[PDB]
Image (tube, coloured by chain):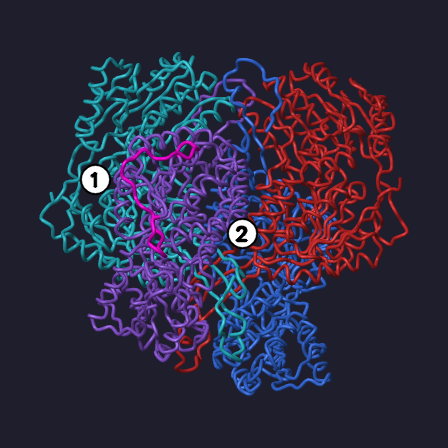
Chain colours: A purple, B cyan, C blue, D red
Amino acid sequence: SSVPTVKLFIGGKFVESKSDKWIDIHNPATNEVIGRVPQATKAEMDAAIASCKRAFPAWADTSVLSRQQVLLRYQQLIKENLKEIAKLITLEQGKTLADAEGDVFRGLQVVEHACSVTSLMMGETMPSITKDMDLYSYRLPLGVCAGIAPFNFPAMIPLWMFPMAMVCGNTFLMKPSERVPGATMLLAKLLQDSGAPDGTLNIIHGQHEAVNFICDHPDIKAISFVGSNKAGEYIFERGSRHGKRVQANMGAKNHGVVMPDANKENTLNQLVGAAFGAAGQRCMALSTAVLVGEAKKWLPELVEHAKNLRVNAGDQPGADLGPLITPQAKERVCNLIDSGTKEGASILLDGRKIKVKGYENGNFVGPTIISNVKPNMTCYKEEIFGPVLVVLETETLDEAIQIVNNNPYGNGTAIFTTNGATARKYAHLVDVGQVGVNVPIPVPLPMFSFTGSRSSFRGDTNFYGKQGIQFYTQLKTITSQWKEEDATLSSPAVVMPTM
Amino acid sequence: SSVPTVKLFIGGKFVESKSDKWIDIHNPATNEVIGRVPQATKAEMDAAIASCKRAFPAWADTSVLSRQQVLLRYQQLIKENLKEIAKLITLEQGKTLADAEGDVFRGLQVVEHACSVTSLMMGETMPSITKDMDLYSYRLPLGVCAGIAPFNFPAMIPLWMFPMAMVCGNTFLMKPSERVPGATMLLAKLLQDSGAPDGTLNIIHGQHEAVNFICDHPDIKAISFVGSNKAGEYIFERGSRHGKRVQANMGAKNHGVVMPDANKENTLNQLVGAAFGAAGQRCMALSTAVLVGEAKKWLPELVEHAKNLRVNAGDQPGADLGPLITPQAKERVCNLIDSGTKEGASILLDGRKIKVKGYENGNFVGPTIISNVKPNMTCYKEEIFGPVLVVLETETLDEAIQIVNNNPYGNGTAIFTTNGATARKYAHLVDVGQVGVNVPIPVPLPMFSFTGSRSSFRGDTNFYGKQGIQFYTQLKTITSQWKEEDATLSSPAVVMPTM
Amino acid sequence: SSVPTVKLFIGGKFVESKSDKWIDIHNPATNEVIGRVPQATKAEMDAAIASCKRAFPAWADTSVLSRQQVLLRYQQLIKENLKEIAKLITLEQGKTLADAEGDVFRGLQVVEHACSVTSLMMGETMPSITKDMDLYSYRLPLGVCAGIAPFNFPAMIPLWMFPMAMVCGNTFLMKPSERVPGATMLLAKLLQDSGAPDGTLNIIHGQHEAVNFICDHPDIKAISFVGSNKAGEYIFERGSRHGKRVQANMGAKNHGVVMPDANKENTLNQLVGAAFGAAGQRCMALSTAVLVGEAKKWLPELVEHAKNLRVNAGDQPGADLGPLITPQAKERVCNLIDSGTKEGASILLDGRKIKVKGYENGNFVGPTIISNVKPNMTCYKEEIFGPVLVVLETETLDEAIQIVNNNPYGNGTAIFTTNGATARKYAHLVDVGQVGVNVPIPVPLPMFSFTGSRSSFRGDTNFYGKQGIQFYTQLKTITSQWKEEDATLSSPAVVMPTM
Amino acid sequence: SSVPTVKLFIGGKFVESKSDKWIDIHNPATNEVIGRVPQATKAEMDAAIASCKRAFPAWADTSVLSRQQVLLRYQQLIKENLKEIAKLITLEQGKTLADAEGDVFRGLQVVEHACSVTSLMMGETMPSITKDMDLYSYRLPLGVCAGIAPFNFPAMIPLWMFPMAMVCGNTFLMKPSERVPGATMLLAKLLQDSGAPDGTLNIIHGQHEAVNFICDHPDIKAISFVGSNKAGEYIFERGSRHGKRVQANMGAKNHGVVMPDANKENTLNQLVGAAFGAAGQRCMALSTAVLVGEAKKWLPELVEHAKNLRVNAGDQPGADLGPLITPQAKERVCNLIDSGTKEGASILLDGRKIKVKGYENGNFVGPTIISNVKPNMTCYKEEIFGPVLVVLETETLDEAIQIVNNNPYGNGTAIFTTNGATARKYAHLVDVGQVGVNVPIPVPLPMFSFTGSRSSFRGDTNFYGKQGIQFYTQLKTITSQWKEEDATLSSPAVVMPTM
């Protein structure tokens, strides 16, 4: 009856932590302790950073072609071991097997995009700016980088963070979430088996202690974070204070706009899948719906569609949404629903008291739909991050756009309509960096960049894409001048260069 | 005997400030008061920000073509008034007419690069990522931007900051240096004459009060700064604290590596021009020279070449370098030279006690050359920002590269040599974002980007170039699905999209 | 009185031609001979090519910055002389003053896009492909280039051809249409006034001898043509035969698809303006209209709207469309209308017998609308190139797309509809390189490229845009290796480079 | 023992040809018949083109992601089966096992570059060019493509041609060289095993009938060729005559410039490896060497180094260069050497009468070095394409540059020197699209495009790189306009769009 311990990854060797404080890993479907992740000690984190620094020079001096082949073999291994990572994700995080497979597939797509380093790391040149003078620039790695991933995406966020940084020539110190480290450990093992030199990738687990270590250590040049607003802002501030570039994606309150001329059944199915998919534990979940004009008549049909969802453990066949991450999240969602009810909101569907056969101890919360919600309610201002859908009613699209713009969180939004003018007006007037036309989850594919907004993102450059490549890299502009008279030594030049 | 007052540019009108606190403008060649710049009051700065916000919507909704026409006409007007701004800069800042004309010409080049907005604001697209699904991204402005420029470039840095934001569709709240506001006033007048809508560009003047206002007001999205390390770090921290993206080019310490096989006379001329040009008051001036191997023998010739420079007022014919900005700068430079002398340094040429005919009251300091300097000396660690050149000697290029890497400031560096292998080795091993091969001032043209480094820059994105355009813009990714069955309404779709 | 003779532009000097063969220039509104253009003799063309070759080296060695300044001043001069060029175009070609101003404005936009040569001429680099090995490429000019422009655009197409090629460093041998050379002469004079070195631009005139000379001379590297199918194919073949890269925009047949849900009045206005604008002599005019489904009911309203057009000389106030280029074009259009009538087609509006007050000698042809046209009719297969609109009726959008794909000409097409799904389906299934959604004239702006198609273009690279820049330039890839051991000569290297 | 017959790859099935004409495959090391390749009949080529056309729609409609995964798995299979293809190449073509491995490795690098289709096919967009108007473009496939590869690269050039067109969405009809079809058969089998739909790739064999079919079939949109000048020009003409874009790489006479300050031993080793590597049967081999100034003294050392090469069969250990392709090539090389001797040339090393132990019947020709060669000699003007090195001598670098510029073939060139000024001067003044600084084989990596020149290349767009994607694709520019008034139907619009 010995609980397995999550191994660290320092210097290319899976080593057990020598710390005293341990964090228990619970299965959200049964709340049973399945493992223990340790809090990395000062000495262990120091050794990890030292290994990253020692591997930086050799890994950077290595040609980009070798890193490309390494990442290609890593993507191959991911393809080979996709179902194992999906099962580990369903076990730790609790999301449905299909959700874990989609997560691993999006991570694989991000890796495959990163495999284009040959074309992404290309610089620029300008010959003959002046007589016998040239100008060109190079893209070079920054140094030791760090990453902090959330619990809702055990595999997608690490594959966003560390592959891009490593392939560009950096060495990454990945700090995965303390609730789902198994996916990150499997990814690190697959990377080590793909030819990655020892010390290039290192992993440490721990609570705010590790975050402070990452944000305070001077040898770390870049920090990537995805998670809540509080932790994201704290990390961004603590990083910028020491001079580290930090890109942090924070909570979101994406709004869905349903126009009267939109496809009824398809729009309702999309709303359901996006609001209750993965138990709503996504930074891109369409947790808010705005029914414009005659769209108010679709509330009964939306509730009927939401009633057809199956709430069961992730590993069970036919499951739609899994349980929540921890009982604390369930209590928070229940308290937020209670507050919404106390503020005058009407609940059309209530799944708080749902009970699953064989999983009575799991953190399950059924689909919840709240109507008559106003912008001044707590359930609207606070990020539910669960299987709850708040619905607002407006008479014109102008009011919907105004409501969307007034909300601080703008990670993404979607408008459903069959009229091109309406979609164009919405996409042009809405102050959201990720707009979706008939698409509820407008997650930009890897070749593009995850375009955060005012409140749902901090920093300057995005996570992946060309933005991602530019973030983990720095430009070295070289102004070269080779006078023609120096090609054949005849006499020294006594004239300073003049345009 | 009334001293002219520098008027504020708020709402497209040159208005005199009602503030009771005034700062006198002294001519550095004679220390005669030639003008006064007021500290903008709270109400005036609020009105300026309100005008910027009111102009933002209309200016952004304006087609990029009209902004390109505006930028082209502004470049034309600058060309028509180049020598006027040059004389105004020579009067206020004190730099020789040649340096002022060069500053204005480089700012004109920056503006002309900005005129390429049409080819730089183009987004990306991806057709048919999924059946009847498309993906694309748009570049859009941020909002009200701000800029804080130093005194050593009354025109170049303002034309780095505000034209880029203007052409991209953003409204700019520019804060020029209190010591040289006339150039910015002339530039704003020429811009208003080019057809820029009233209120699009607003200018305020003041001491740390205005900086705090800019860094604290929430309606400001981006801040650009160039200057010292203390003020740069302060502004960057105060901005990032409030969620604003900030790019701050801080102090620098450039090193000039002289190899034995380099062109003797040309290398010496370049070193002299870059160390004493513009009175050494430049962030890219080669205040440090590293004589590698047999380059030690060139110290007498370097001193002889430096002795041929003419120190006179900026408006006198044949003036090579003008006086310093203020007597405080002269006192600081003299105290730094004294400290260097105390620490064992050897002064080969001393210009502290120089006296100019007819300008005995000016802040003139002749060419100064210090030798036997070590990395641990005050004159080496502190940014002189004046007509002083500290020389170091090394037996091998490896030691020079090590010295350059240990130095925190890496704004730019130059290596002089006729061997391609040596230049390549230096450019590859040196940790400087701007390397120069036989080029003493490796300032990248506006088409490239000013690639800052570890200490000479704080932020993620550079000032001008593609990075400059990206800094003042944000990406809006749009994912649209247009299922074929919706083109010919026959029956509603009851199937959710599946990739 | 004497008739003015068009001067040749050789060596920067407007010289009178010694040719014995002359072509009269007739005013299309009164058929009065307003000028004569000579056929350049063999010696004159040889001298022009010699001047181009002599100017090539100096103009190419000239830094890109100087060429950018020259082109900016040329754009300024165009802005200063826009109305004069428009008046000259209205006098020679006959198009309305507004049409000539739009032509000159589009040419000015093309020039302003060309101003971005600094960012467009950028290359690529890949540092450290192997140990001590670098790789980069450069964009360089081709050499002497030539251009053959049609009559329908005396200014737009010349400004597409010669400015783009010249700013990249090439020397252009322009060849304008023998019917409208005055606009090209004025443009060349303005360019010479902008500071362009003499001999960089040379211009000759001729019908077939000049074309054969341009296609046969070996010193010409690139040829740009716009016009009919016969001449385009002939020039393309004669150029490819001699190893010259040739881009030839040929005739077109645009189809306007009108869906039932489109904006009735706006769609009709756009159709009228695009079918009868500029006397329908444009290569992008919607000479064909496809009424899908219930769109058949709009034929009476379309005819009524077309009846409101004013047919008068180009210089008269309120003139909507001017006369044709020559009596031969009028006879051709009349014979094509007669053939269409003889093939079963129905004419709703007949303007062949139109007579204008005071301009009875002008080649005026009123708006003509043909209905019941089938794909097998002569008027449908032949390019009318006049104020004639053939209307077809389809039962579904699939039939319209099939008809559009079956037509060999695909220069451009437009679909009018308020449903986004329909527009997406059309743009995806239509085999046309330039599609328009509610836009009748989908002429891409300068920053994009004029994307030819199956029959309306012969070649690989487009005219303007990034493709336009690439067409008049060639890549020079430089694989440079500088071993570190050569930086410090100690012993010769006896090992061949190995990956 | 019966001779194995090469199979045709039509409709995704390896089938034997019913043609009565067969071409024997001879092992160049023993001239023994190892296989036969049939000349595809008219019916078989028609069926192949029909399969390509039938596969084009489904393959193009397939998302780019699926094609990316297909190319990734194909690169994986190539990595797995690299040694088998290398052995097949050594057997058929005769090149050393190391040469075949390098061929397959470069082809694999090209495939990996093609895997970046997600980033290369991305279009452009310019939002808000006019009120409620957008503009964007899409990269789309052309159609059925064809390829004709030479014998000296059984795998490298096929992997240049067909993978690029495949991943872009085009169906390819690859015609490999009749002398080395086994490598192409293995590559097609591996591709079919990688998930490529049946009929997407088709292969036919022949000498002239297949070429005429490819150049005359109207369903073929693009043709890619590499080989001799005669065949390249013939194919380019026959293609452009029918309206097909053709890119044809042709013979080369690359020159190697050796400066006195260059690394003696390393330069000589590089010259030997590049002139005699792969038996000189390469389009980038340095068959010409220019000894500038004091470089004349290195002829004895060059001959001594060339004498150390081992001439043996490709599959034998320690082999440096294999035998020629056919006895006709050996006879041609010997006759060219004889003609050069008759014209006054001096042969320092003669390998014509070389005899290999155990391979007396093979087409082996030892290293040959010719000196005192002039530009007007036959051996200089004619492409030897064998293990022959003609050496020229010049007193200054200007003379060498003039000699290189006067030569028509400019596929590539290399200059050896330790002085940056000389290298820059050469790279700037030499009229060659591929310049090498201390690199004998300046073959651009797949990320860069092949940049052949005046006589060594015909066409507009280059083979691979971004140019490769641009060649096998076409841009579809879409000018979209959605007026805001149409989003909320209230009244029809009676105003035509106006800027």
Q: Which segment is the magenta one?
A: A10-33
Mark 2 or 1: in front is 2
Q: Nearer the viewer, residue A363 or C132?
A: A363
The answer to whether residue B88 is seen in the rendering is no
Helix, strand, or loop for circle 1?
A: loop
- Distance (Cα) linking label 2 and label 1: 52 Å
- Describe residue A3's horizontal placement relative to residue D277 as left or right: left
- Residue type at mark 1 is Arg
Residue B448 x %, y %: 43, 41
Which label sits on residue D118? Answer: 2
Identify the residue position indicated by label 1 in the image.
Answer: B179
Magenta stretch: residue A12 in it?
Answer: yes
In the depicted structure, whether residue A492 falls above or below residue A387: above
Q: Residue furthest toward the front?
A: A1
Q: Position of residue D123 (x, y in %)?
A: 52, 56
If the image is split into quadrants, where does the N terminus of chain A sit?
top left
